[PDB]
Image (cartoon, rainbow over all chains, first blue to last red; front, side):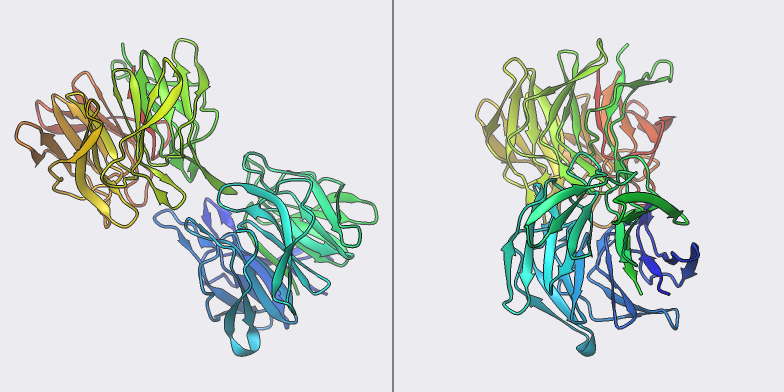
Length: 285
Length: 285
């Protein structure tokens, strides 16, 4: 029995919440707060430990982009700090390969990174790898076939529909088939050997369309849309279904959690977060 | 029966409010929204039409500097788009001379402009003119003796107390006496042939001090301070008094409107906006 964790987020300001949802009984746990409130961060799990990467402390009386990496142990309900990244990365994306954390893109003030760095838990160290072809913030990241895909985002002047993927053994990036839709701040995850891109923001609108990339046909295909438009949503896969949590629909910070069943190509609302928020990090362990 | 118009502004996100205050009876009108929420814009009036120039649209899912120029007709309650500027200008200053709009300085991402352009309503065209000596975002702008004065601001590294002056017939800029206090995001206007600079940010605190420039003596002199510290305030002159609207005091987004009477050298709270905001464009017609 694993839990869906949601860390940080934004509503009026950057949040400290760590909460966990149990899809099997519908309950929500309230865990220890983050040491620093952060939105636009990403979550991942390595060796049973939850990690919060990057983001931004939005505060009335000061905004500060985060280069921090923090590790939460579900057995002890405790956060510990780890080595910081080389640069602050707000609206970061991350993926894990072989127990290593890849920090992709994100922004530091007006600087929109294309740089990518890699965290080795055993040595508590970051090291830069090859930079992406495109600068990308609000970028979705997915790991598929031991490759690191970077989908959509915002390069500092346009929101993007392009995607590229990274070859860890070769340390190089190649562009792949662009999506049907321009998307920054979409939910990007892997489910049954496909990359899903759900929701997002094209500079004017919030999306509810969802498309998935099939590797061997190099095609993006639309699937069923979500019930709510959302940008800056959290996303994860638990037991063969996609969960999207919160986000922003243009007027509301959502507390809705929708669940995508790939057998019926159907979305449904399965729970509500304890309060509406966007820009969360999400992971399952 | 001229009204004080306040357009756009910022509270957590950029706003699209067009509201008009009547200093005679104390009432507030709610006029048609801007098509695009914008903060850090400026307002000005040419031939009875209200113009909204530049700024930036902050939203929880991403930000977009503006190069837009929009024209609001009080007789029709309708906004019409105009030709855009050559570049986006957030934290812009504007002044009007002979029915032409000068767009001064401001930022686009990492770029801090010293460029300046001129809009001709009769042609719906913008044309570049001589750039300032200094790059200036959050610059105050006032028109006096058919010259364009650019006061204070932020050059990308430091906040400025310098000020310079533009000669339309000669197409050139000249530094003038610098102010006593460093000020970005001050309110700058002309009352009784002097240039007032009210509030702003000195790189450390928001200010409530006000100083005025006498051209005959080339000197800046403090007058009575405002009661509330504020940077990124709106400002205008109506029937011989200075009105400042909203701003930011370092924690709160003010709704306070203060009025300065030069005969008595005293400020007074005369009304409150319908909600606290900073970074508005203001003009009277």
